[PDB]
Length: 245
Image (tube, rainbow, N blue to C red; front, side, top):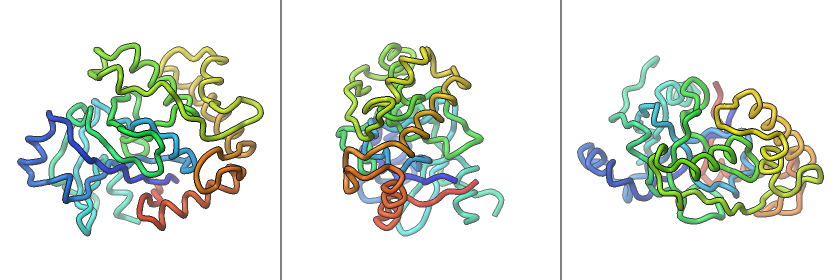
């Protein structure tokens, strides 16, 4: 299914502090992670934030050994099966997390934050979405929408990094395939679901089968060869795990 990426919450947004303190959860001693599903572990170098949804109430679940996972009930269920209902420690709306600072595995970009995405599926994945605007058309379009409507989304405009670091070279779409595809397909909105599904498949196929890594341990290797190795490295290093639905 997916790789679940453990994105560490390092500094919680002010609006969330009372909550975390009320529940005796300290993000500096305890390891509290947002668990974001991805199909493309090799793109984790290019994370520029992570996305949660204000439309979702997340559970905070005790995963064991000092680790806590922030995700939907449904996804936590699926992780544990690998009870029928798992009670969280507490629940938290995505809006409450916005602006929190995070450490995302392998990301070269610094000072990452939790940002909103209005199209994140609750019924698919974990409710938390990795953000790699160089290579994910959805991510590129949401990033552009955030920068254009910061008041709507409840963010600082300068939280959106619009200066993208290339991580995969393709001959067909350049070094930032998502930018190329979104401009060339004239995709206007995060809500353009069918168009974005098409762009995503194009990006994934060209990137995976014809891409070359520009960064990390496997720099210069084909994505096709690198990606399972990046996956295994993340898993061995405790930064990720496999998530099936």
